[PDB]
Amino acid sequence: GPLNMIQGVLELRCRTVEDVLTPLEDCFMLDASTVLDFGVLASIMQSGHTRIPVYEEERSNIVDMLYLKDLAFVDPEDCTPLSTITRFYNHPLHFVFNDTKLDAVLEEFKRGKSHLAIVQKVNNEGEGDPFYEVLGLVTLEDVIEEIIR
Amino acid sequence: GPLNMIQGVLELRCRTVEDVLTPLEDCFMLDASTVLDFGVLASIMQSGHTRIPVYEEERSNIVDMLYLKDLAFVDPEDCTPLSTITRFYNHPLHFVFNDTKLDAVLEEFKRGKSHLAIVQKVNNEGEGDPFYEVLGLVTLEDVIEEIIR
Amino acid sequence: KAGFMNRPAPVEISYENMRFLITHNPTNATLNKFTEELKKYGVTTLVRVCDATYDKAPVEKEGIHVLDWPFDDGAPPPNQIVDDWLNLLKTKFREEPGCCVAVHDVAGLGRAPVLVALALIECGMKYEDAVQFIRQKRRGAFNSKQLLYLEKYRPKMR
Amino acid sequence: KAGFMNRPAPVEISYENMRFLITHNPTNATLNKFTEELKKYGVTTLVRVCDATYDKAPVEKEGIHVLDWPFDDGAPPPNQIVDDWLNLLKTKFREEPGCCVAVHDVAGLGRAPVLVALALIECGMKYEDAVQFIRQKRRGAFNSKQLLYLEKYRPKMR
Ligand code: NA
Ligand code: NA
Image (tube, rainbow over all chains, first blue to last red; front, side, top):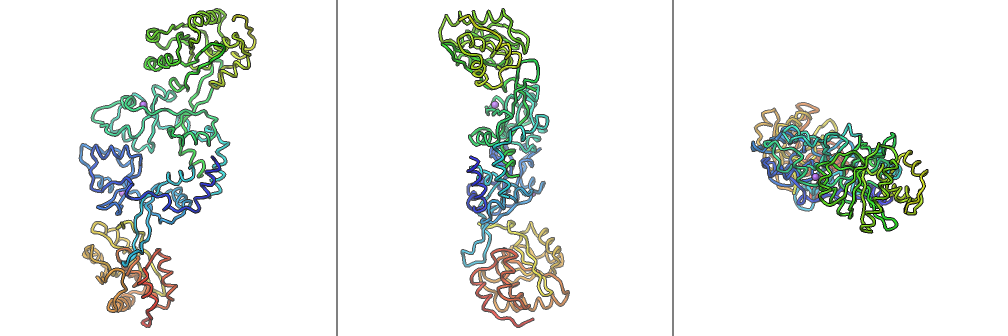
């Protein structure tokens, strides 16, 4: 009970974002080339997510992020691409390195920042120049449930 | 930091739902007689809530609850009243007495039950027969933020 | 600011080969599910104690004897009405032992659980055990008037 | 699976009356904001070290000298290119002391921070302090090859 969640909040100080993330393959994401028809809009409805990433030509290249309020007066009658809405509003992207402690990015979430965080890790594993690999997404709910479970 | 939230989870065992509720007057609610036009649908979009109560003729008489996924393929072109959608899907209402400890209704939330709870208190303060007064709503986020703040 | 469909579920009381059910007030659109619960608990007889806010035609069409016995709010039942009660339960409990009789006011924290409370004190159970039984089944049963009346009244009629 | 607009912000390096900026690779739709950052940091000279994936026409229209000096990935710069570097910084640092010169590869964890690292070791700063400075500014700077090259090379040219 309350004890288990005490060990939860105390274990926040050790566990990294990489232990709680969800890989890109399993994340619900939107291509910037999609058009807000009845089908996709309905998918966003029944997605259970209010902030959805918008990528360009590759799940790894996350360009912007679509909030549920952006769809306020959008009608599928006009075949409206979501990229237009992407340049309508400007919600800033929040990035986080894989080995960030959960307490920290928690305090980042509480410090105003968006409840969604794109997770990156440096990849020297190759003879080319180091680069940032996108592992996946981590959200407030992931951490909260990391303490209440 | 982690200490403050430890005292948070430990204070869950004392504080009642009545300390964390939001009164009915301030809750975002839908009349069962409203029709899902562009305006109201947009309000639901920009409401920041995924589960919204639906009352009948009085904010106190909460009849059903509308989930965001219920609006999947609804088009405002047909002036569709939300009561039809209310009898389309059947999400069960979760009720909670005012003096319930926060840890408890927290475990109720985690036990599958809907993240929204209608709060009631018995009112003997009158010469008539006792009745249940609706004080307001309490949600998962209210309790979570009761520990992370 | 009270509710109509937001009251908790009806409660079943079992004592000394007797089965009651305290429930709340329905509304015209609801009685399909309400009498569904009635037939679920096996009630053959329903006693409405609040004002008429529903049509008795459906509930009597399902085969439930309904008896409009209203009296003023917050008050103890008149002696006529407690007579009717006790005798009614003698007849309907003589017709089928184990039948559930149901009674409802606005919400089952008023005159209805009072009447089942008198029915409990006349079947051999103590006053404190009766009231604690009923409001242990659904919290916050009766007001001060109904509890003082409940204490100051004496049983003899099996 | 890497990003294009998901790299962190460019980093400004100040040392011994010198101002560099390590940044990443843009794309045709982006350079308005990128060169906006360029003019923000006061860069007069941009050195592109990765392949050409953007048009130099806008950035040169804003008044930024751009120099396409590419070499193979993961590798140290050729001696020709480090010559050009050092002399370039002599000229553009002689034209306006305090001017920021910017350099970019795919993302500023490659040849670009290497070149600014050599520029740092030639201005009087130690090797360990240089590399720790740069990757303290943006984590994960260089690979093993670039770091071994960075250690085994000696400075003389002010
Ligand atoms: Na945007
Ligand atoms: Na429903």
